[PDB]
Image: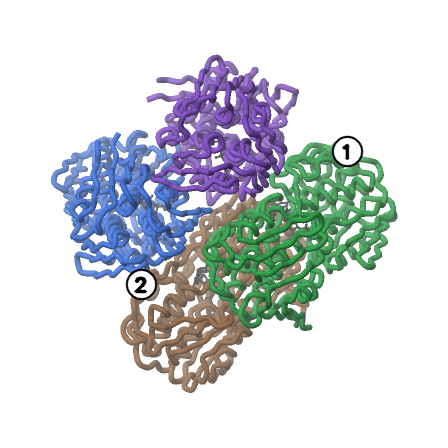
Chain colours: A brown, B blue, C green, D purple
Amino acid sequence: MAKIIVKKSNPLKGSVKIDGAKNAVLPIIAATLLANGKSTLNGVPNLRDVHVISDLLRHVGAEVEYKENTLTVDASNIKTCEAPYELVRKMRASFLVMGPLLARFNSTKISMPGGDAIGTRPIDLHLKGFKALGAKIEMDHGFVEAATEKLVGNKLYLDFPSVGATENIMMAASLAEGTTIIENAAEEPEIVDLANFLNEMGADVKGAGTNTIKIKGVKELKGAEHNVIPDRIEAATYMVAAAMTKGDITVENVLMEHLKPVVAKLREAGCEITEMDNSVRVVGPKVLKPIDIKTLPHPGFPTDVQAQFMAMLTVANGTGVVIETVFENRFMHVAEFNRMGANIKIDGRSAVVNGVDELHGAAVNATDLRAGAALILCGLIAEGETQIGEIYHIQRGYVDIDKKITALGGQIEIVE
Amino acid sequence: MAKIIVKKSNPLKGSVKIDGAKNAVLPIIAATLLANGKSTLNGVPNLRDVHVISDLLRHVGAEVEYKENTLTVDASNIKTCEAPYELVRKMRASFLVMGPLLARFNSTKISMPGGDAIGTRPIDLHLKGFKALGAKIEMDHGFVEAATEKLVGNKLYLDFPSVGATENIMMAASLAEGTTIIENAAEEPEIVDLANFLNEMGADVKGAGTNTIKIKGVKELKGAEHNVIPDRIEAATYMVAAAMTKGDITVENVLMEHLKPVVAKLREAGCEITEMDNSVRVVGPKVLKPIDIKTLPHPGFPTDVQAQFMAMLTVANGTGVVIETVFENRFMHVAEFNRMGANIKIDGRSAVVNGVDELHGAAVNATDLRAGAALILCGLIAEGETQIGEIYHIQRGYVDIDKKITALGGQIEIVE
Amino acid sequence: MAKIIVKKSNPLKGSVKIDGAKNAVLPIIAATLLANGKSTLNGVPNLRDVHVISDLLRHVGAEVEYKENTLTVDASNIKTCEAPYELVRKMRASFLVMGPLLARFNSTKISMPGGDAIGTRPIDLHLKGFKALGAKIEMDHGFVEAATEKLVGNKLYLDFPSVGATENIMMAASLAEGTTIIENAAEEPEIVDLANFLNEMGADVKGAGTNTIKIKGVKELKGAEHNVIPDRIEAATYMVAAAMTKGDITVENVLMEHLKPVVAKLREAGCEITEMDNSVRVVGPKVLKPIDIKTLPHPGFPTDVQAQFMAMLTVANGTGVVIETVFENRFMHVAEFNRMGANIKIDGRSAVVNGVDELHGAAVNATDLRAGAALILCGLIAEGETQIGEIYHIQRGYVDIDKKITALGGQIEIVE
Amino acid sequence: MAKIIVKKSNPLKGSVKIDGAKNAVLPIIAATLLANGKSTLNGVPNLRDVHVISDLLRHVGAEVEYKENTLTVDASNIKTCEAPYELVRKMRASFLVMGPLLARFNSTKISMPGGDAIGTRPIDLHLKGFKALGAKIEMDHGFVEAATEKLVGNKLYLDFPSVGATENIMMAASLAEGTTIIENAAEEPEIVDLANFLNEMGADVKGAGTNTIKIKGVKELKGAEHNVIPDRIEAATYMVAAAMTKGDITVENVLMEHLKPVVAKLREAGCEITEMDNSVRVVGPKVLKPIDIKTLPHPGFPTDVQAQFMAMLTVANGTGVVIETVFENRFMHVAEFNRMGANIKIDGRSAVVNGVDELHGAAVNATDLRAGAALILCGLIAEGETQIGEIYHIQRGYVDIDKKITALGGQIEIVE
Ligand SMILES: CC(=O)N[C@H]1[C@@H](OP(=O)(O)OP(=O)(O)OC[C@H]2O[C@@H](n3ccc(=O)[nH]c3=O)[C@H](O)[C@@H]2O)O[C@H](CO)[C@@H](O)[C@@H]1O[C@H](C)C(=O)O
Ligand SMILES: CC(=O)N[C@H]1[C@@H](OP(=O)(O)OP(=O)(O)OC[C@H]2O[C@@H](n3ccc(=O)[nH]c3=O)[C@H](O)[C@@H]2O)O[C@H](CO)[C@@H](O)[C@@H]1O[C@H](C)C(=O)O
Ligand SMILES: CC(=O)N[C@H]1[C@@H](OP(=O)(O)OP(=O)(O)OC[C@H]2O[C@@H](n3ccc(=O)[nH]c3=O)[C@H](O)[C@@H]2O)O[C@H](CO)[C@@H](O)[C@@H]1O[C@H](C)C(=O)O
Ligand SMILES: CC(=O)N[C@H]1[C@@H](OP(=O)(O)OP(=O)(O)OC[C@H]2O[C@@H](n3ccc(=O)[nH]c3=O)[C@H](O)[C@@H]2O)O[C@H](CO)[C@@H](O)[C@@H]1O[C@H](C)C(=O)O
């Protein structure tokens, strides 16, 4: 079955355009279910996960059409409010339809997500929020059911600033009676994008991007047209690629405000970075300086760039420590990096990376979306050739990584 | 030597006035060193740690006068910029004079803090910030020295949203040439109070309380008059006391905006809480519902109320999990709680509290400020009598806890 | 694709015969490569992993024949000493041919194992041991190569009492010149079985099952006939099944000496256990008492029964804590148990299990061998029907679990 | 108050005689309470902790006499079986009189140990064992009471191979009716010494030093004469001193069998070690090679040499990782090492030591017995002078460390 073949490459040089954010568009697609009319989403990335959630919207009876990076949803005449086991198992972001469906129908039944490659990942804080809004919660044979005679706005505190729980509860709150206050809200840029979309549909959401979100519920929302924000994680991936290959890459159609920790840490590692209004230039250093990273809720260092930064550190000039505070098990890639000659030792949530002279190409497997991209970055600097398996992990969340890296001068091909 | 004797008490009832914040006033006292004139701080709590940092200001040559909760500092004619080993060992918040002294003199030498009861507690992020502003850092026999021909404003990223590093770097930045940007800043209320004081002296500090602080440096600051914010941790201590004793307590001279996670979690445990503009009423439940707590950077659940909430949970109606993400070793109190008949098991940063019918009075020792207060709360509900040793831990950070609890109906005395 | 369907079952009752140990036979099959003649292994379990390592022996040029639980190996005329990427990826126990091949040929090249479902799982201690015996170690594009002009016996210390490193180093030492001492050796029963087999071939291995193994190297080993020990993990699985179903099961063809922690902990949970010379009877309690388990090196509680005991605890009468000290990531099953209505919270290496009234059948996926068996145990007690996917995990290490449970009265079928 | 002053020293050279084991003699002194007659213990080290437990024996009514490294106990006419709060707080090894007193009187009441510098340190496994022998356990105001009409031998499993629980339960079992089996027993050398002493008094204890101890109870024990084993931790301290100072030290009156992991790891770091029947010679390397250490139950690497090895690693030629699996909080020394210019970063139970060119003398505080000795070792290699406070930690468990190091050529003095 299919492989990505990467060879030892020249320093990457040129421009790369970044696609629309996967993690902005998935919650915004769920949010289209809130509205009694037709939404138009522009800058949608052509990714399998976008097409899976589209099929979940079709399952509940929305009219969905995709072409040329535009998705339209007519949720006027939704029929059903159950998300079946197969769709939630394909893509756990399926769970983000629970808030809108509860808000629209006052009842919903959603398959509970199971095991995940990067950790246990419970959805208790989502349920906490729905209960605070007056929903009664029951489990039935792997499904979570939430139902109420009417959602009522209430104050609630998030024990952790969960992205998904913030999104699900903001969407449920948008049609509740009265005012909801989410305390200790996630501050991620995708939260702001979602809130902006809800306000475009006629909602009243204030404070997104701060620690407190206030939602004043409205009776009805209407379809709206929205431009999704750029993918800050894809942008960061190409920025790391410039750092690791001693390259010179201009990343186009980005928002620097969303990349601050990645810019800071790449500068600490020795990159020269030029921030512009719609683009950033990254010049890799001749010697990578070892740095430590600690993943945290935004605007701390993002867990979605942890594997990529770890790959950079495998050839840094000394010892770097990577601490993962956000996910339990997000070190599955370490054994694959070690197959390529890295020197990485883990205990608990910390990995000690002892820089080596060079990586060596080897047969490796993608374990998840972001680690698979980290393996491509390893492959560009590893002596010889690297063959990466289980490539569906990568292909589901990066648009045409083979074409984009090829245009920057790298040696990469997908063999089917 | 001295003991606090607590007996099984009646439900606490009445009003308690909260003192000025220890953790607001300590950095604000350091900040008075920035100014060429006389500052006046009102609402200063009469605590030993306030009197120790006052003696450190006298050591560097400031004129300090304390009476009736007002402290005045004339830093016009500071002489020296070294903080010796004895003062830093007495109180590690001594380290917060490093930023102001570097900013005033372009040189400072500060004893590095050593072991602490609640964890290792490095000051690497403070030094990271001073280096970003152009200081060269050297160690000499237990001292850290920072020196520059001139501080220059620069962008810098905090790997963790350290309270102390945020404070130290904001104060150093206030007299630097140009603009400093602190990314991933601490959002704690004391950060806002300090920033407000710097702006009262003539600084230009924007964004305090958000994830990004921008400081535009000025050439000179002038003495100013400031009213310190209330002590949110003392307020939380009395709120927990009402919860544990099935009491009814109005906490006076507080800011509800600063207590949101404590209010939320006490409500989840079954308290009825009435929030007013300058006060909060807490009515304890007849049965405490078990809750989980996870400490986090503000506005997440504060590590400074973790031991007190754990004490509450020792008699809750089931199993509660306490996770400490902020400090390494902040479970030293567990063995003292277990001497009083608690059922607490720890592994790593998590403690599993299995509620018991009642605690039993025993001889126990305060291990640190907030745990010592938690032992007083245990003592109010424990059958018989509790004798608490090593009481300097408590007395250094609570104003007259014996008099305040006595006025709420509790049985407590300090025996010398 | 294929599923295991389990229904809510009657209490299990009857006898079950246990097969030969998977984890005894895999290293003993590698060990047959040490000998210049024909070995005969009896009591070999009919498992896919036995058939994969058999194909690896054929790959290096041994004559292998399997029938009716007997495997014969003629390693007289081995040809090659490389274990390719495909075979090591299929089954990481492939790596155990490295010691014998190094000992026979003074050179070997083995694909380094990559990611694993239950943790990173480095093989550094194996290499440490080969280096101590005089091998030079090099990496080539995902392979580890070990080579020497002659293995020489030496003292070496294991930083952790690794089962695999103990096995690999004992086998390499068996043909070395002089005496090897393994300090802090694994004490697992399979170590003793392997040592007994090496001594049957003419080796000199003393101390297996203690903390120190002494190997005096011989010039030549000869094929021998060996009876593999019973599978203590399969035995423990059926013992837990009796505990969870309030059953009464006699487990046949077992060694009680190998099951001591499982017997102790089942007795603590309320089981009545009768230990006999070749069999054990387990009578489940009417109420399961909550217990804590901490996995450790033998003769501590085995990590290979951790998921199964956790499943038992999901319906115990209170709160149980499971700590995994042996593997990093061995909690992937928790999310599947939670789909069936368990109440399990993890942080770090500890899981807090809050017993529920009953589990509910749901669609779940096996994540690994022992967790998949734990899901079958959940299925026997869960209301309704449970459908388990990814069943190759189970089928590769349990002989006919459907037929054995069916004969004890349970409702289980494999649908293809 | 009192300080230890250490200066930058010459390489240590010469012989040092090791004293009797503190951790052998403390349980053996408790064990003298089992006997109706006079015991004679030879090779007792002249330490404060020996004199505290002696005062506890006097408290319960034993006749105790100490002179010239010989302690005699006549426990013929013991009166009382309570260990009061003051004595247990002075020295938690006081708790080891619980087993003998329960065995002699069928009742005992012992103050429960509270907080400790190196972790929580519960005594649940001791109580588990006493309950298995038929004792009923109750808590009364900080005391644990154990009482029975008669101890009866039973099988029991230790969830962790606790040294103290093994000792306490073996001593209680020695006078029980019938046979006790301790499964997953501690294997530490002090367990063997204690068992040998019990057998000298007329007990029947088999398997000490293995994973299973069988005690066949006797009706009466008689006073006996015993030679305590050497202090393996003191021996290891001087061995590390030779390693760190590039010295050449013969450690006299030791048992190499008890030092295997320390010898192995010092050899891995580059020491040349000569093992003899009663002595070991350690020659420090000119460059220390970085090594990793993981503390474990004997015969794994001892937690009591972890701080000392960490100190060695602060100047090793690269990066070393220290993992503490045995104690929770045993990293309090890290902040003191960092005051001396070390580069140590901790997360969870792991510390990353990045070797520096040299340490610099500074004012530091002992946090516990073994860390305080590690600070002396730092002081011998640190530029200039080191002043160590809180020296009672050191003096309570090392005999004349100033005189022994002075005789090896080091510069050390105690100033009072
Ligand atoms: C669709 C989408 O946006 N997915 C992203 C979002 O996941 P989400 O699931 O919302 O993230 P969280 O809830 O903030 O999870 C953060 C932490 O909080 C715990 N938690 C979360 C929810 C809850 O109810 N209870 C609870 O305990 C949770 O287990 C985790 O440890 O945020 C993550 C963090 O940045 C990203 O890694 C993730 O990308 C992924 C990889 C991808 O592109 O495939
Ligand atoms: C004077 C004062 O305000 N002290 C308070 C302040 O400590 P501070 O020291 O500033 O807190 P941090 O820097 O936010 O520390 C948070 C975490 O960050 C790590 N870190 C901190 C700084 C650095 O350079 N490097 C680094 O790694 C650090 O080790 C810790 O794990 O904030 C703490 C957290 O809320 C409080 O518990 C503390 O109160 C105390 C108890 C009291 O009243 O005695
Ligand atoms: C074939 C076989 O016998 N496999 C078994 C054996 O694995 P092994 O791999 O030998 O186990 P370890 O080396 O004792 O591993 C124990 C720990 O030691 C770390 N370690 C191991 C080796 C090394 O070089 N370096 C190193 O750090 C390692 O990462 C782990 O955390 O022992 C395990 C522990 O009981 C079993 O779970 C495992 O069964 C499996 C599931 C199955 O049936 O599929
Ligand atoms: C008097 C004496 O011999 N003391 C020593 C002995 O302590 P002990 O207390 O017996 O050690 P453990 O019981 O083997 O403790 C090991 C681990 O087991 C947990 N545990 C222990 C008992 C129990 O009931 N429950 C439980 O959970 C415990 O918390 C720890 O994490 O063994 C330790 C380990 O080698 C030594 O560090 C210690 O020396 C000291 C420093 C000194 O010289 O001052």
Labels 2, 1: front one: 1
Is the same chain shared between marks 2 and 1?
no
For badge 2, the amino acid type reads: Thr
Residue A292 percent across, percent down from the top left: 47, 47
Dot 1: element: strand
Viewer-nearest residue: B31 or D78? D78
Badge 2 is on which residue? Answer: A212
Where's ligand 2: which quadrant?
top left
Can residue A380 be seen here? The reply is no
Residue at (50, 60) in percent of width and height: C315
For badge 1, the amino acid type reads: Lys
Disc assigned to residue A132: none
Is C155 situated left or right of D320 in this image?
Answer: right
Separation of disc 2 and disc 1 at Cα? Answer: 70 Å
State yes or no: Cβ of the residue under disc 2 lies below 8 Å from any atom of ligand 1.
no
Badge 1 is on which residue? Answer: C216
**Marked residue chain, label 2:** A
Q: Pick out the residue farthest to the front.
A: D149
Tell me: residue A401, above or below residue C219: below
Can residue B32 be seen here? The reply is yes
